[PDB]
Amino acid sequence: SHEATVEYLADLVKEKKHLTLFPHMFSAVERLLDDEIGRVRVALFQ
Amino acid sequence: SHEATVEYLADLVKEKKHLTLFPHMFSAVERLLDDEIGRVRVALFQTEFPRVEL
């Protein structure tokens, strides 16, 4: 999986923002993104 | 990690197709989606063929 860095986190959060403009049109993608954001946040501080 | 089934794989593939409407706009997501598709294909394959590991 991708290296954890604040830059990556920022991309993930920005891409997540954009998709919320289309309610539940990319439901699977949203779960993946949320999972990966959570994973990267934890990695950043450990 | 989501359960591996045919319907899920199907949803993944449809979502990937939709994302092509947005070239170069969601590339972090493209990598994640391709990873999850691969993982799911492998999971369905390992379930048909339990004695094969990849």
Image: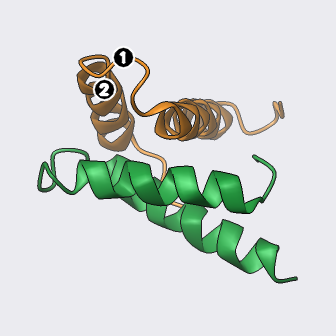
Chain colours: A green, B orange
The residue under label 2 is B19
Residue B1 lies, in percent from the top left, at: 56, 62
The residue under label 1 is B23
Task: Judge left or right: residue B50 versus residue B44.
Answer: right
Position above or below: B49 against A25: above
**SS category of the residue bearing label 1:** loop
Q: Nearer the viewer, residue B42 or B22?
A: B22
Residue A24 lies in what quarter of the image?
bottom left
Residue B13 lies, in percent from the top left, at: 35, 26
Task: Judge left or right: residue B53 versus residue A37.
Answer: right
Q: Do the residues indicated by labels 2 and 1 lie within the same chain of the protein?
A: yes
**SS category of the residue bearing label 2:** helix
Label 2 is found on which chain of the structure?
B
- Residue at 25 percent across and 45 percent down: it is A26
Badge 2: few (under 14), some or many (20 or more) residues near its Cα, within 10 Å?
some
The amino acid type of the residue labelled 2 equals Leu
The amino acid type of the residue labelled 1 equals Pro
Residue B48 lies in what quarter of the image?
top right
- Residue at 29 percent across and 19 percent down: it is B17
Position above or below: B15 against A22: above
